[PDB]
Length: 226
DNA sequence: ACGCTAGGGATAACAGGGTAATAC
DNA sequence: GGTATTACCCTGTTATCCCTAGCGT
Ligand SMILES: [K+]
Ligand SMILES: [K+]
Ligand SMILES: [K+]
Ligand SMILES: [K+]
Image 1 (spheres, helix red, strand yellow):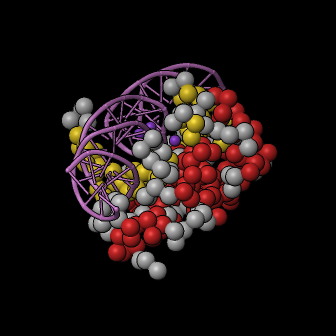
Image 2 (tube, chains in turn yellow, purple, red):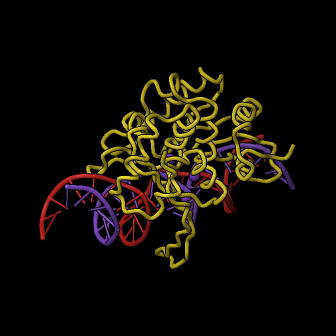
């Protein structure tokens, strides 16, 4: 009946760790739907030749946000989030927070579903069979944006930053999102790569779908003047 | 003058892989 | 006393979210 407390600082190949893992086989509904959003967003779902099952590597600027994600996947995360400071070619110090799950079979289904030749890809049935409003909220906290950053604007158009996907992949998302959630998303380009524009007249709908899941430190991505 | 949005910046992501601690 | 495992930590690189100049109105 192994407590995770005890795994803290043990060498990777410790028996206690392998015995701890069998206390879990599949992601919860909540974890699965969260994680579908995060994969579309900011999470690395990682399996190289060296890895026996998928794990997650987490990296965010926002401290409250990474600590929230770690609580959702609490079981799978041994060590707390760690501040990392890097110098960049400009010579400026950059701060982020980092966390990792261990490898675990529970991550394999979504790992094989999303990753193909070490690229994230959009499966033709992703939207229909997997994306819920919980998934949409996480995708939005990760990769979400305003069309108009003027603080006093009346234009409440929003963006999902899908630059890393293929045009034809984003066209699938837009088509299936508009059928499943009755949105009027349309495609646009940012540095010649595809993004999802959510028009102003979808704002009340989108808000009412995702706002229930948005944590207090992420409401700003969604909030305009009334 | 003002509302929108295409063009572009320095990160804030996303990645891939080295190091070193248990099991035999 | 190699060899297999593998959590944590280190290094590469840039497409991101975010900002704003400038055009149509
Ligand atoms: K992404
Ligand atoms: K992001
Ligand atoms: K960035
Ligand atoms: K990026």
